[PDB]
Image 1 (spheres, protein in one colour):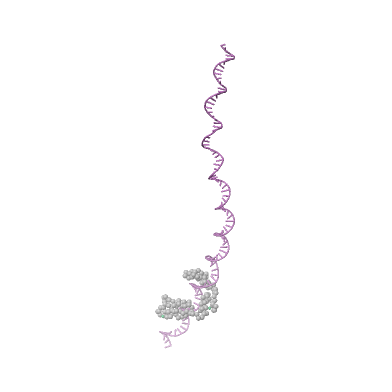
Image 2 (spheres, rainbow, N blue to C red):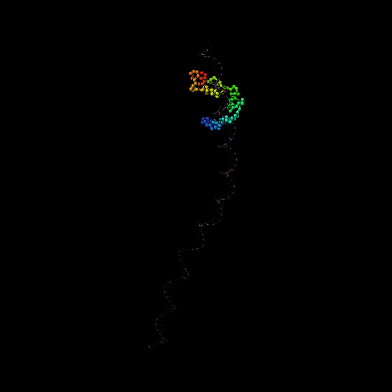
Length: 121
DNA sequence: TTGCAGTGCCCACAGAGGCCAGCAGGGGGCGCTAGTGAGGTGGTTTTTATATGTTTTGTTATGTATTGTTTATTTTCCCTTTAATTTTAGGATATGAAAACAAGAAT
Ligand SMILES: [Zn+2]
Ligand SMILES: [Zn+2]
Ligand SMILES: [Zn+2]
Ligand SMILES: [Zn+2]
């Protein structure tokens, strides 16, 4: 485990994908990459029978599509609710990240440093 | 009624941001095995140790040989007394040698 861990600092990727440029830190990530070229798909969502490449994708599918009463995530800055955490990530990166050079209002001279305040104005 | 100045509405293509699969990042827990590492047991020999038999060493007793001891028969040194043995006259013998006599021979 520690031998495998040290590549997280160094960056060694001693496992090459013979069919593309990808290179993984350990055996499992390479075996998981192989399904995309071979097209093998061992796992199956038992409810809708929709097809997926990856187990975790299926688990998130079940959680968002065939599950009830699941907790959501509220943006701290704005008042909108959205389902997935990673989409809350992309929301904070595209709308509430600090914009260095600023953006000016289309109709007045006021300049803003966050896209949210701009759209709100 | 119209031209002009200003408004309403409908569309649409952009723009935007949540939705979504895909995919890669670090880390937790299991399936299985090669390869030593060490520890324990068994076998082997072996080595120390012990006991028995044989022989070697030490001690004891008997016989032989050596040294000493008072006899003890030589033996040998020293007397006084004879028994040959020697020496010195003294008389007698003998054998010689002159001496006298007698006998040839010569002058
Ligand atoms: Zn590849
Ligand atoms: Zn499903
Ligand atoms: Zn927000
Ligand atoms: Zn403005």
